[PDB]
Length: 121
Length: 246
Length: 239
Ligand SMILES: [K+]
Ligand SMILES: [K+]
Ligand SMILES: [K+]
Ligand SMILES: [K+]
Image (tube, rainbow over all chains, first blue to last red; front, side, top):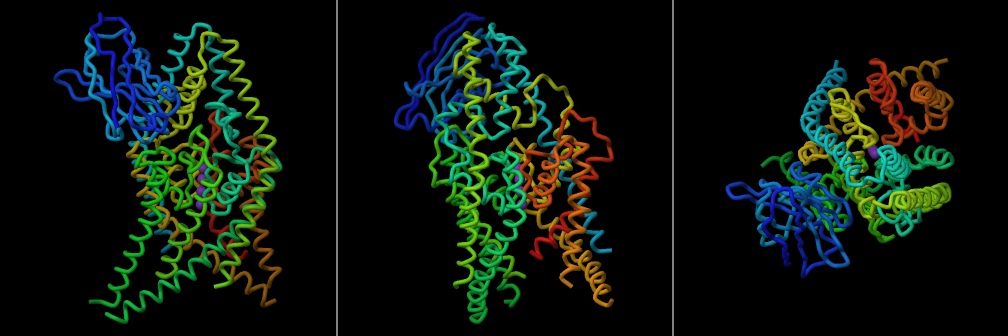
């Protein structure tokens, strides 16, 4: 029922920062969750996604720099953002899908959503 | 000059179909080709202890197991069997119904010899059950629509509405409701669930989405044979409609 | 209502019996393959300390994601997207209307899945009209041949089925055995799996990406499927 993000900070260009998303009120292992972002003046964009286990999928703009992961034993999801560019400063929202088979990339498939966390580069 | 005309229509339908499928899948294939090449380069960059040849050997070894029927994802020891009583019943059902998913196919020479004789004698055996159900159900439907026709714009028109009603009920009981069940159990999207039911009930069976084992999670032994019973009653319901029409 | 139920019991018994035979034939191979891949993954992590066990699974899943889409993760290809070109998409369209569905190359996009549902719903009955039309014109030729024999019936019927097993089953299997490089069993297995519209996809005609195929080969195979599917339909109707 509820998604909570934590880790929004201010960072220099070309630096690394990791943000977290914790699920509560639902079976964490049965939901495939992912990350999204929205820079001022721009529409919502896809960032990263993961299935119930270890299958990840990224946007062409963040592959090789961003790393989505999950620790089902701790009911959490982490997004390690490396070499952050000034084009990555956006409100990062974490969302979840009842369809866990593959890492979903379309925002239409994600059912539950987070409040967002401001990462500024 | 009638079968040849149909042949031309079919060839045109394949050329037209080929043009549409090309435009729908060419950009995704190009993007996936670029993506996998980048993922392999980034894996070697992140893991300095792995040589580029050692990476290819691991990939080919995973594909060798995947093609044989064993998924290389997760703990294979903890995973269930694809040839136990429940899964081999669904494999047998997959052969006689001509669906042929091709996900868990025979690899042994003995398994290939028995599969030829199992399809040659099993496909007509299933056809006798499928026709028998359809003819018994067509009699029930014929009696129900004759009772409706006795009460009643056009005698032909009243039979078309009944035909539409049978298709609509079948599309809810055997198409809509099962797709909702697969969407939650397998974890597929709403589009993938309908796509699966259509591919299955039309005996196409691509194998890209399979009712059981489409994850490294432990599926119940009674779930997979129950899906074949849905296939049996679904294939048989539409056979009674076509027998009533003919 | 005690005749269709008897057939149902025979069919269920046939599936349980079939399941017992297939289990005994494939259980030792599956067990050996499960042990093999588990050992290869454990040895990869032992040889490569810098790789975590989760990072290994993600790489495998990523390679399988590309492999299932049609792109082989071994080495590197090029803009040669010969899996969705005019020639390969024509055979995929045939794969759908004939209900064979090899599934070696299938739609991944949402649009491709929406068009595939409407293509099968309107294409499978369209192909059925051609398949019945060929079979009825073919059945008339059969009737005229068997009436000529009767003028001079079960033996004649058996002879007409044995002729189909040579022209459409034996001869094509010999051609595939040399061209593709399959064993004698694999060739018969392919022809049986194809003509019975099962189409597993484990053996595909013109699917070996490493063979320089001649232009007259792939469309000739689809002509064989078309003329073979009508002759095989008469065998299954007789049985
Ligand atoms: K079929
Ligand atoms: K099939
Ligand atoms: K198939
Ligand atoms: K298949």
